[PDB]
Structure formats: C-alpha cells, structure tokens
Image 1: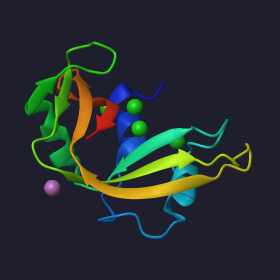
Image 2 (image 1 turned 90 degrees about the vertical axis):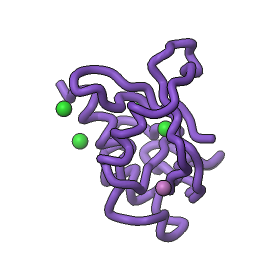
Image 3 (image 1 turned 90 degrees about the horizontal axis):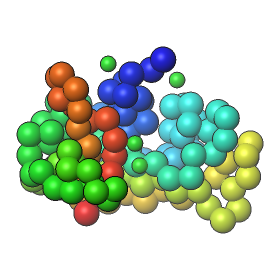
Length: 124
Ligand SMILES: [Cl-]
Ligand SMILES: [Cl-]
Ligand SMILES: [Cl-]
Ligand SMILES: [Cl-]
Ligand SMILES: [Cs+]
C-alpha cells in the first residue's frame, strides 16, 4: 500500500534536526516512525538534509549497489546522518538502539518518474 518513495521518506528522512540529538535519538525515532511496531528493525539510517538535497543524489555519481544492481548513486558531498543499530541486549517489544552520528556520503538506489530514492544502500 505505501509507495516505495513514501516508505523511503518515512524510514530515512529527518530534516527537522541537523544531527542526532542525544544517545536516545534512535530509540525515539525508530518508534515514532513506526519501525519497532511489528518487530525491531535491526539497522536503519536517518538523513538530516532537506528532501530536495537527498532527491538530487539521483542525478549524482552512478555506482553499483551492494546487490549488483546499477541504479545506485553516491552523493558528491558528505551529509549529516545518524546510524541506528539494535544493541546486543535489545528484545522486542523492548527495542534498544545505539545512536551513531556521522558525516558521510550516502548511496541510494533510485527509480520511477520522477526518479527518486527508494532504497538506502550504504554510507561511506
Ligand atoms: Cl509517493
Ligand atoms: Cl506509518
Ligand atoms: Cl538503513
Ligand atoms: Cl531502505
Ligand atoms: Cs552537505
């Protein structure tokens, strides 16, 4: 039901903050974005740039996706991101995440018309 583009936005965009606040940032965002609803999503990255800047990566450097697809694009500059990863002691429904703030290039897979990000492949 949710489109691939809308799901990308819900799971990865956080333009309201320039960077991960506290160490509690991942526990509040994984929950508020309904990512701990049926289970604990194990890993997830949030991008703290405007939607328009993330969408423009689809016109940047074309690289291979980890899965071998060729519709991946690496951003030219680094972006503010937050990595959210379940801790060894996380157990649904008590999901617990480690927040790691970093500044790096993002690699996204793009598709459709308009050609927008539909999958977060990795950061470098
Ligand atoms: Cl959409
Ligand atoms: Cl939702
Ligand atoms: Cl991710
Ligand atoms: Cl994804
Ligand atoms: Cs930037």
